[PDB]
Image 1 (cartoon, rainbow over the protein chains, first blue to last red):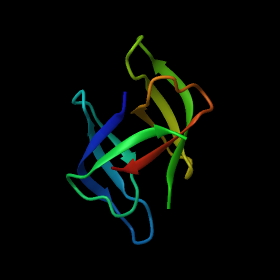
Image 2 (tube, chains in turn orange, green; image 1 turned 180 degrees about the vertical axis):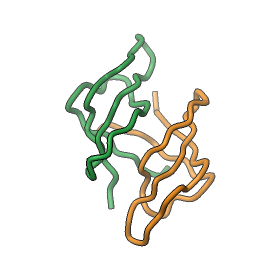
Image 3 (cartoon, rainbow over the protein chains, first blue to last red; image 1 turned 90 degrees about the vertical axis):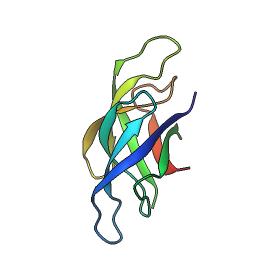
Length: 50
Length: 50
């Protein structure tokens, strides 16, 4: 199934640099990750194999 | 730019459940995340806004 997490906080976001975000997975687990530029609190990201 | 991380270790993987993995982002940072079922060490995942 799809692995998605909601952006809870943007912790550190330099210009032209991907931010550090704290995200919450659908099981309720919260973790720090790197997320694409432009993401904001309340957005959702997917972790997908490439 | 794209945010990708290489799967370094599968820490916990129940059947029919997404595994806990330790991944390494392109800047060298390592973090625990949830990754899709079927991912194995050496695969690459992308974090993408949906």
